Image: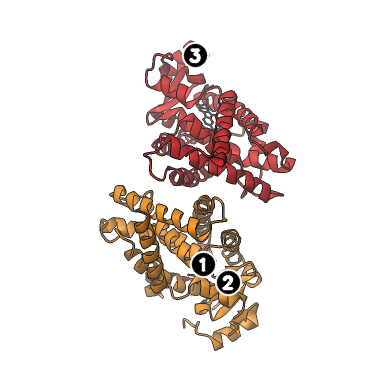
Chain colours: A orange, B red
Amino acid sequence: ESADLRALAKHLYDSYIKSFPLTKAKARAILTGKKSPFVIYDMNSLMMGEDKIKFKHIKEVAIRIFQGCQFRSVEAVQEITEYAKSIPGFVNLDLNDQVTLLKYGVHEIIYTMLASLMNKDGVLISEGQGFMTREFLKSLRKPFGDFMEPKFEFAVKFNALELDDSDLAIFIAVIILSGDRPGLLNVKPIEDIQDNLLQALELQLKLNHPESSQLFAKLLQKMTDLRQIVFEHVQLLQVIKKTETHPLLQEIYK
Amino acid sequence: QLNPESADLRALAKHLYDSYIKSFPLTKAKARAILTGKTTDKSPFVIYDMNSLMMGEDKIKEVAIRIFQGCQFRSVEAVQEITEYAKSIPGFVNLDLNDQVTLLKYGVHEIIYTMLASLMNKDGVLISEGQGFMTREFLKSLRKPFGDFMEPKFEFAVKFNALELDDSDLAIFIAVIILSGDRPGLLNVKPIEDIQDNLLQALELQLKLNHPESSQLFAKLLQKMTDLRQIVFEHVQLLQVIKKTETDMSLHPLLQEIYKDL
Ligand SMILES: Cc1c(C)n(Cc2ccc(-c3ccccc3C(=O)O)cc2)c2ccc(C(=O)N[C@H](C)c3ccc([N+](=O)[O-])cc3)cc12
Ligand SMILES: Cc1c(C)n(Cc2ccc(-c3ccccc3C(=O)O)cc2)c2ccc(C(=O)N[C@H](C)c3ccc([N+](=O)[O-])cc3)cc12
């Protein structure tokens, strides 16, 4: 059984590597020092990064940034979908259930992985070629300035766990196979798979972090912070439905 | 398997179970004995309508307002019980006082809904220390916004009760809930976290011994936290509606104090 647990952990790791270009190890290497990324700390550096970078979706700053985040989210959704398909048992599930699990899981996964790109002072952007400051994002006009902040608070807590990519792969898989998403038709094989994934995660944390007491529990506890962050994000998405500022574009985004 | 550290963990579990029994008059064992017709305990009077509500007000020790007040009183008593219990958790009273206060303030609701599940089935809830049973439909028939108070608690309780926890499991789980290091405004997170870590080891051991053929119960239980916090938030929003719709109704200052800054 342990054999299958480690084989699973490895499979998931390889698949995570193939699906997500910018890994946590890479991101960390960039954030600490190892070809320094362009830094966006204010208006002028933003404009410079627009001209010198590849972020023009051919007019107010906060709205442009928000839309960028949108575009990148749609890409992430495709990457996560591809990863989900590699989870043993996943494609064998009822197709409606696959859709439901992805639809409810992508936000939680996006914030999880976003933590890998973040420190307390900012977030790697543009494939890791840039770094936008926390203070700059906070300085954005309301309510756009309040979007990223809760996520920095989450990431600071989450990053304290010092998980690596091989831990994260399994964790993300556990997140996808959540039996309590609304509207599931057949919960049983979902919870069966998830229980296998949770055993794999347990073994992984125990081997990879022998000195981290109850890391498994703390990680599981982080799911509360994730769901909360997702709820809050939704809550201020509703507020943006004020702000009177591409119908095909309006179609591409959920 | 038997060894020194795990012996310590079992000792902690026994301690907590013992304090739990001492602190909470109405256990899940007694609740279940009452709900399932066990001869250890007497049968409850059932309130399912206004008529039986009026018969019950006699046979038992505006309508929605009166029910809500009884619920208030009971909640106060529960805060007292949980506080008493919290003091027995090793290390809790040694923490910074303000942090003890914060921990209680945020833990009390999550615990109340957790234990409330013990008194529930899909059809209703035990009341008046188990002498009564108020049906789910009757509570749902109450005038808005009072008719929507209890439904979420029921849904949560059917889910949570699916875990089949007994009192000895709950004692540790409740201890784990109290000692959450992510409560807002904590001065000293670390010692809280060390205690919770010990409590989590204890919970893990307890579930694996008490539910051997129950795969990943520890994980499922920990995941119930999401359900708890959602319930608490919905309830708080509903109370916000209440305060504005019924300015003639008095909320208890202890409860108001728990609600301030949430
Ligand atoms: C995947 C992802 C990355 C890499 N960043 C950092 C980022 C990404 C792009 C830029 C950027 C800005 C300007 C110019 C270029 C770039 C650039 O990096 O390319 C900066 C930081 C994110 C920030 C927020 C979210 C988020 O909250 N998503 C949820 C699901 C959501 C989001 C939105 C909605 N919604 O509105 O409906 C729902 C759910 C997601 C991401
Ligand atoms: C501790 C507790 C118990 C045992 N029950 C079941 C119950 C308790 C008492 C009765 C009862 C009803 C009528 C007559 C006698 C009894 C009886 O059992 O004694 C029935 C079931 C509860 C139900 C709801 C809440 C709750 O959400 N409280 C918050 C703080 C709140 C609660 C209320 C309000 N509010 O509306 O003012 C705000 C916030 C708390 C409890």
Binning the other alpha carbons within 10 Å of mark 3 as few (below 14), some (14 to 19) or many (20 upward) gives few
Disc 2 chain ID: A
Q: Quadrant of residue B195?
A: top right
The answer to whether the residue bearing label 2 lies less than 8 angstroms from the nearest atom of ligand 1 is yes
Q: Badge 1 is on which residue?
A: A114
The answer to whether the residue bearing label 1 lies less than 8 angstroms from the nearest atom of ligand 1 is yes
Q: Badge 3 is on which residue?
A: B60
Q: Badge 2 is on which residue?
A: A123
Could you say whether the residue bearing mark 1 is in a helix, strand or loop? helix
Type of residue at label 1? Leu
Type of residue at label 2? Val
Disc 1 chain ID: A
At 53% from the left and 85% from the top, the residue drawn is A53
Binning the other alpha carbons within 10 Å of mark 2 as few (below 14), some (14 to 19) or many (20 upward) gives many
Structural distance between the alpha carbons of marks 2 and 3: 62 Å
x then y, percent, for residue B32? 42, 24
Type of residue at label 3? Ile
Contact between labelled residues 2 and 1, with CB atoms less than 8 Å apart: yes
Residue nearer the viewer, B208 or B31: B208
Are labels 2 and 3 on one chain? no
The answer to whether the residue bearing label 3 lies less than 8 angstroms from the nearest atom of ligand 2 is yes
x then y, percent, for residue A184? 32, 50
